[PDB]
Amino acid sequence: ILGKIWEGIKSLF
């Protein structure tokens, strides 16, 4: 996972 917290960020927008 190169961005676990990013997975949700890209999902918000």
Image: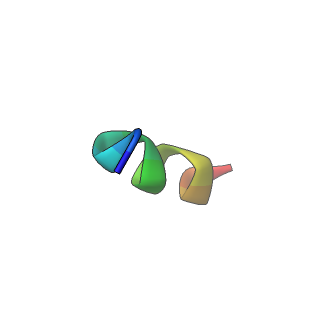
The total number of labels drawn is 0
**Most foreground residue, 11 or 1:** 1
**13 vs 2: above or below:** below
* Front residue (pair 8, 4): 4
- Residue found at the very far front of the displayed protein: 1
Which residue shows up at 31% across the image and 48% down it? Answer: 4
Give the x, y percent position of residue 9: 49, 44
Residue at x 34% of width, y 51% of height: 1
Relative to residue 12, is residue 5 drawn left or right?
Answer: left
Residue 10, image x, y percentages: 60, 48
Percent from the top left, x then y, of residue 5?
31, 43
Does 13 sit left or right of 9 as displayed? right
**Colour setting:** rainbow
Near-viewer residue (3 or 13): 3
Residue 8 locus on image (x, y percent): 42, 55
Q: Up-down: is 6 above or below 11?
A: above
In this rendering, the answer to whether 5 lies above or below 12 is above
Left or right of 12 in this view: 1? left
